[PDB]
Image (cartoon, rainbow over all chains, first blue to last red; front, side, top):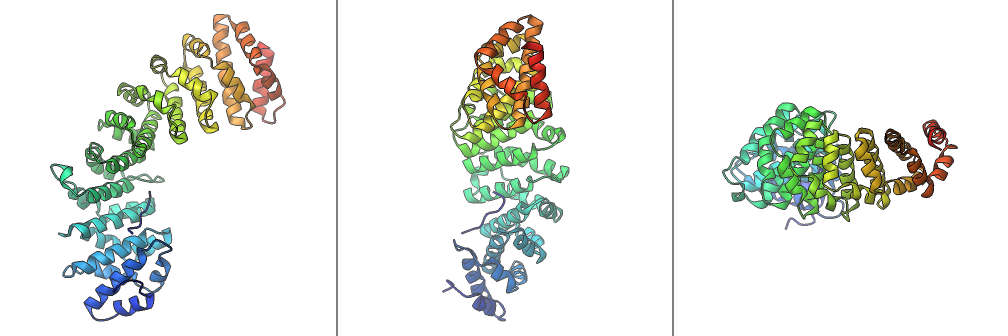
Length: 7
Length: 425
């Protein structure tokens, strides 16, 4: 899980 | 109001000399960048909006625009390495670090998230975030008597960003940074939230993926018992990183592997070696293979926990990669084990599956199996029971496979099979 977008 | 804006309208609003118009346009950009399907990150970048968002990060007198710009930049930084780089090149790292100390919890959380994305890009941006001084404010956010008083999502995001600061190699994180982070990491590893536990285990697995000095830094903090306890957990997202960390640790010295053994890890492997998740079985068998490469007393502890039958089971039926890890475990066992341990291995029924696996196409597993069989034959020689072992191999159909390997392309397999046939057959 290197990066996550905030929806 | 701010739904389904065009990039042109967002640009017009952000370029106005009106802070409220800028806030509304920034919120429209945040909503665009927060949509499910293909958020127009590249379009937003080409419009030149990153510097404006970065400047808005510093509007202490307008916290809403700070939050909206932090969210937009977080989502931009969540994309490709080029998009994260565009965020970094706009000066976002120091602005987000300054926002870490914001009195507004949601703004601080968004800054934590953004720094997590940036650091998660890779080692270079990880170390750059560290150089800008992120660790001190990040850890200060967690300097509370009881972690349970913090919001669940806030704590989860902090744990995830810290795990990204522990992540990646070539180079691994700076030693001083790891030492600064580790105590908070242990404290998080004792938290009750499943996601916090999972991400703390992932961080520990990153920190133990390296030379024995890093493994030692981790193990000296006394986390191995907690890692074994989590290895026993029901949530697969926790078991996976805990098992990864335990495997990493047992790749180290025999003393660190013994630290793993003393914590009671072997008692979990009956389930792990039969786990219906293929990845768990493979990782557990790899851990077992690194444990059987240890001392004869450690091989003996493997025997006492009744794990040799489970290795025979994995060798008999499992995914081919798990079977390869099991072959490696058997070869290490036979290389380091006593004659008594090797004859016990044979008595558990290893020969038939080990021979059935000689029909695989991969060369390396064939070499591993041939080495294990050579070691077993050497033990038999020491006991003078070579003929019984030869009869066993000939009955299960292994002699035919060995003769068929005499005509193999690889020189090592060729020579090993011919040597076995010339010595014992």
